Image 1 (tube, protein in one colour):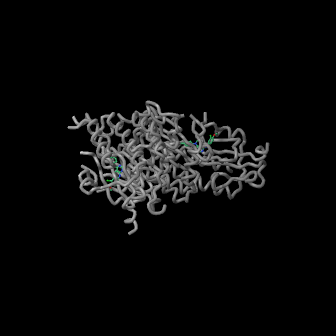
Image 2: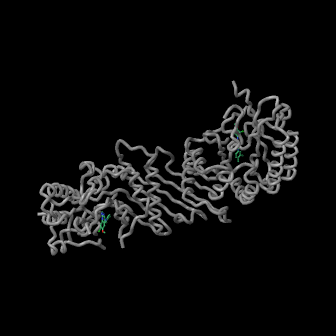
Image 3: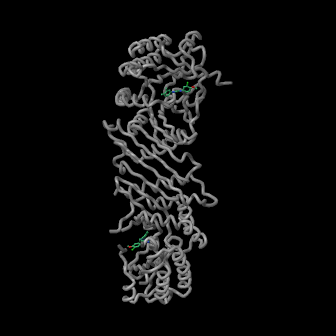
Length: 297
Length: 297
Ligand SMILES: COc1ccc(Nc2ncnc3c2ccn3-c2ccc(C)c(C)c2)cc1Cl
Ligand SMILES: COc1ccc(Nc2ncnc3c2ccn3-c2ccc(C)c(C)c2)cc1Cl
């Protein structure tokens, strides 16, 4: 697939170039308006590695390098995950081959919005020491191969890179991914057996994160919820995840009826209210937090 | 200097890309019409490593890779010589920092001529197993930084990368480099004390090489002659050179009045007769070989 080739090639180039750039003492205003573009033309050469004619553009390379650091991600590890082997498609989005990252096609509009929030996003991240349920935006690029132009973004996978998820929801509190929905969560009677301390830590993150979203007039986000079943996985020792990698995982409590491990975080935030030119951002967050607070009562 | 930066950067990229390309069982006709171009644009990014906006084009990358191999040169070694440290200028041409290679600015006309002869050049090289006094053309590029476009070519240094040359001539047999000339060779009474076997091997190379030149209607070439003085170098053990690296070196004979080592080869061949739109190529070679055969009598 020529678009994955260019992505793998562009990321590889992106990180290697960056390896020559000094880690700054701080980001500057201009860092949030910067880009690197590269255009390759091979005439009668290299027909076999990948396409002869392509472009690759990286937005705000210093910023996303900074964010990778703040999210506990090493540039060389990142490069490896995206280049050692091709991303795996999903009937859409890809997964890095080691399942650490999601690669997702987005619109120019989405790209523009990511730009409009990137300063506030950064600041929010600093302020919370990288501990948040918001998407972790790791890099953002434009590809051209042939007359096909596309925008992609890379986020941390909400789910474990190792523990399998036998059941998944996407919750809004009121096209779309292969998940179960609000109504299904309700009808199924789905419970999440985590302790009071873990509910408290989780919700107090959610409340701040969501408030940030409302302030930005963003909407239509949801809480992605994945359940690993441990006794099923019998058919790091069993039930274990590295928290430093599987950053959204929370163990069930001692009295959970089933040995579960849960992966919950916010996804798909880049819809601005005005872009819908219904529900305002305030009403959306209010419904959203009420539903989440509810299903975790 | 932004033009050396782009060159170092372009070569580095050139060889690394090539490291992914399979060594072919043979060159194809299209290999001699091929190129790779790359254009970089950095807005508000990477201001410190090198220029923000540049282009780099490599001509016939498969061909010059082949020639590097046939001349006993490993691609990674080549890359290192040109990138580990900046080329050193000459008041003009540069030297690779380890003195193995010459980098030389040339005209588009020269570039066009290199192209016109590149097939015959290749064939000639094969036929003689790489043993020749002709320039060893190792790579050829176009650089653009700012609105400054330039063409460069890389050849093997005629002189030792290690033994110093205290005296240099550029001989034609009838602007210009820092060398002594025909008349000076004559007035000085300059002798070259090599044995009959070495004269014979050298001249029989020269005769074939020069004949090749005449066949191509090339002109205005010369024999670059450099003398290392061994007793002076007292003010690999003394007098030694690796022939595999210092490919043009010939030891003086047992009865030379002074312990010398000599570096002789042909340079500066890319002038085609027609380009001068005097002396024809035949007369030029005839004068040239007669003078060389003469100074080695
Ligand atoms: C087998 O099913 C799954 C496997 C894995 C996942 N995990 C994800 N972790 C984080 N972001 C994600 C995903 C999926 C998509 N996105 C994502 C990214 C970025 C944008 C901009 C948008 C809109 C979505 C979700 C599912 Cl369903
Ligand atoms: C200190 O002085 C020197 C040190 C070193 C050298 N050695 C060289 N070995 C091979 N080609 C060379 C040179 C110099 C130039 N060129 C060269 C290359 C390519 C083109 C196209 C043209 C015209 C010349 C010569 C001198 Cl004088």
